[PDB]
Amino acid sequence: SKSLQLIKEHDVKWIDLRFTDTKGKQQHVTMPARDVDDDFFEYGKMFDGSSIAGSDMILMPDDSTAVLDPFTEEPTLIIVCDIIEPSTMQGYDRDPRAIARRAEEYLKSTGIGDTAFFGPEPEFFIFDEVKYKSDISGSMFKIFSEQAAWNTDADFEGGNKGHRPGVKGGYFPVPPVDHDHEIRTAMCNALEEMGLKVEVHHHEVATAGQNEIGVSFNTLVAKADEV
Amino acid sequence: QTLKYCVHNVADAYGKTVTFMPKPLYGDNGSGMHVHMSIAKDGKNTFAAGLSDTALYFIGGIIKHGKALNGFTNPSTNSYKRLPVMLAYSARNRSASIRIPYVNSPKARRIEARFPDPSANPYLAFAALLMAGLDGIQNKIHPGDAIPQVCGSLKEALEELDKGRAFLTKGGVFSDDFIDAYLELKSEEEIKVRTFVHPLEYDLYYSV
């Protein structure tokens, strides 16, 4: 199918099966590419979900979302998988992807419509470093950022180029002021290599390196995987 | 002058250091030298909200020559980093540059002016306040009822002093030559302060 075609095209060596826990943190388990066959797609892998926050459960791959990984030098193909209960062979009750599929099927069953379109724009922060601890002794979340508005007099390895965005004034500065143009371009390139149809990227309102990369829309489960 | 002496040396004794400039801090309260004026006459109190008409004329003289008084009671480019600016008087209001404390005795009735700052020379500031009050009393200047504001920069305060020195040069209390020399000194001082780069300008305009 799709995954086999990509494996043949790019000589993929590893298959990375990815799912999502309740907390929303993506989980991945790797496997050799030589094990991909009919039985891999009809049975899936198995793993112990007991230590996942929220026993044995089947990782059933979804071949419609096979996409190359642009970070690993070894060519690895990423496959987003569903969680199947071995007792019932149906989608897991607590699997967020299964819940999203159930929601889209409910939408197409009530007759209101089909293929609900979700386009999310999430914003993120770029920091040079970050430190945080919290124990009986004390707590702290010190934050380090060369482009931060509070570093106007700091000492940097290389120099303090005093061009930096002020607080609540980092919205659309030119590259001399925003230190994140090239890294945002690299993020956009990686997203495109992962099949994401990006549409805009810029510096957000915040100082200390807030960026946004808006990408194109899709259906419920497709957009969840895309996010 | 003795108070400044003692405070400075006692600070030095413990290794600390006292400053008397009105505003050594931004983002926090400055320091002001409030002045309580109370003219007496043959042992009685002239200023007896309980203020006689003469006290109101004194306040009117202070109000009328407020910017010209700012050349002596506020002879500092710090003084206008602190500016109690509204040149009005009240007995309880905290937004008036002139206040009348709730004295418990009719003998101790006095007015308080809040714009002067400790950086002012005591002799010159006190003489300027008294001369303005005397002018207002002699000319029967009614202050009104409980709007002008004091100056906002030493440049305009010096300009107003140059244009309103007339009441000081009454009876020879202030010589015109002394006022001219004082104005030239303060003008060179203000010029020195004004034409020097501010780090806030590096905060604002460095990238633009």
Image: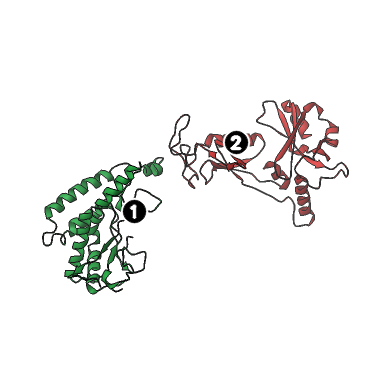
The chain to which mark 1 is attached is B
* B126 up-or-down from A199: above or below: below
Residue located at (72% from left, 44% from top):
A222
Viewer-nearest residue: B114 or A142: B114
The amino acid beneath tag 2 is Met
Viewer-nearest residue: B166 or A163: B166
Q: Are marks 1 and 2 in contact (CB under 8 Å)?
A: no
The N terminus of chain A - image quarter: top right
For label 1, the SS is: loop
With B135 as the anchor, is A217 left or right in this view? right
Tag nearer the camera, 1 or 2: 1
Residue located at (74% from left, 28% from top):
A14
Question: For residue B93, what is the image quadrant?
Answer: bottom left
**Where is residue A198 shown, x and y percent of the image?**
62, 40
Mark 1 and mark 2: Cα distance apart in space:
53 Å
Q: Which residue is mark 2?
A: A187
The amino acid beneath tag 1 is Ser
Q: What is the crowding at mark 1: few (fewer than 14 residues within 10 Å), some, or many (at least 20)?
A: some
The chain to which mark 2 is attached is A
Chain that is coloured red in the picture: A
With B86 as the anchor, is B162 left or right in this view? left
Chain that is coloured green in the picture: B
**Where is residue B84 shown, x and y percent of the image?**
33, 60
Residue extending farthest right: A87
**Where is residue B131 shown, x and y percent of the image?**
18, 62
Viewer-nearest residue: A180 or A174: A180
With A101 as the anchor, is B178 left or right in this view? left
Q: Does residue B159 appear in the picture of this structure?
A: no
Q: Which residue is mark 1?
A: B31
